[PDB]
Each structure stands twice: as structure tokens, then as C-alpha cells.
Length: 129
Ligand SMILES: CCCCCCCCCCCCCCCC(=O)O
Ligand SMILES: CCCCCCCCCCCCCCCC(=O)O
Image 1 (cartoon, rainbow, N blue to C red):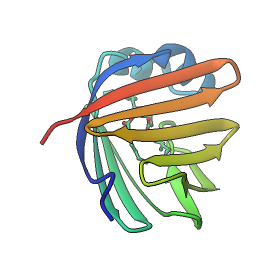
Image 2 (cartoon, rainbow, N blue to C red; image 1 turned 30 degrees about the vertical axis):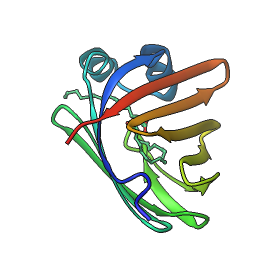
Image 3 (cartoon, rainbow, N blue to C red; image 1 turned 180 degrees about the vertical axis):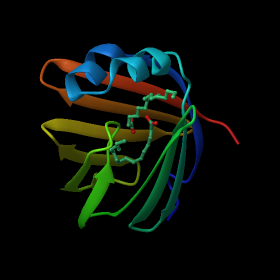
Image 4 (cartoon, rainbow, N blue to C red; image 1 turned 90 degrees about the vertical axis):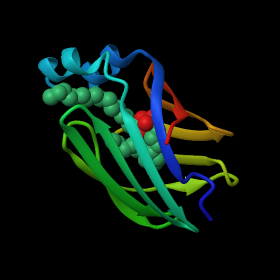
């Protein structure tokens, strides 16, 4: 239904280093990645989502159907089995490895909040293309 469809680039983020260290991202990628303004491409067709996250040379492709089991490839390379849900047209919610992820679209701005214990990793992206 394409509410989420589009290309978005990171503008700013909070707690990137603390989060990525916690989840087990190699430090050399943490250091090279902290100032990258990554691009996220989303194609939504009803309940069916495809998204590509590009940060440098690194490209992660994922897909899921809302309300069904999916297999998501995380930043470490670990693939996790989970379910992604919509809470209204503009909010995607999921959990994996004790991390709660909330992706919310407001016009042209996507806010993604990933919470692991006390660590709240927040990314703000802006529609490009
Ligand atoms: C070899 C160059 C280094 C590349 C490593 C850069 C990795 C940066 C990580 C930023 C991507 C974080 C995306 C979190 C998932 C999400 O918010 O939807
Ligand atoms: C790399 C781990 C995948 C992230 C898990 C959340 C999956 C549901 C949301 C998919 C839309 C992705 C939006 C990206 C926004 C952003 O780059 O911060």
C-alpha cells in the first residue's frame, strides 16, 4: 500500500557506538560506520515489505510479510526469526535478541528506535530520491 515506500538517508543518530558494541559489531566497522549517512530503500506492497540498507560498501537486503514469521539479517550478519507488525499505516514494530525496534514514518521523516536494555539507539532519516 506503499505508505513506507521510498529512499531515505540518515540525517542524525544517537547512541550508535554504545549500541553496536553491545550487539557485537566489530570495532573497525563501528569506527568506520559511526559517521556514515546510510541510505534505506523501502518497497511496501500491502503487507509485503522489502528493504535495502546501504552503509558504505556494506549492503543488507531484507524482506518480511506483516504478521508472519520472517528472517531478518541484522548488522552483525546474524539472521533472526521474528514477526514484524504494523501499528497503523506508519509504524513498524518488532523484537529480536531482546532489542525492540520501532520504525515510524512521519511525512518524509523516518524515526527508528532500537532499545536494548537502557541503550536507546535512535536514527532519523529524510526522504531523498
Ligand atoms: C566497510 C565500511 C564500513 C561499513 C559499516 C557501516 C555500518 C553502519 C551501521 C549503520 C546501520 C544501522 C541500521 C540499523 C537498522 C535500522 O535502523 O533499521
Ligand atoms: C538490520 C536489522 C533490520 C532492522 C529491523 C527492523 C525491520 C523493520 C523495519 C524495516 C524498515 C527499515 C527502515 C530503515 C530506517 C533506518 O535506516 O533507520
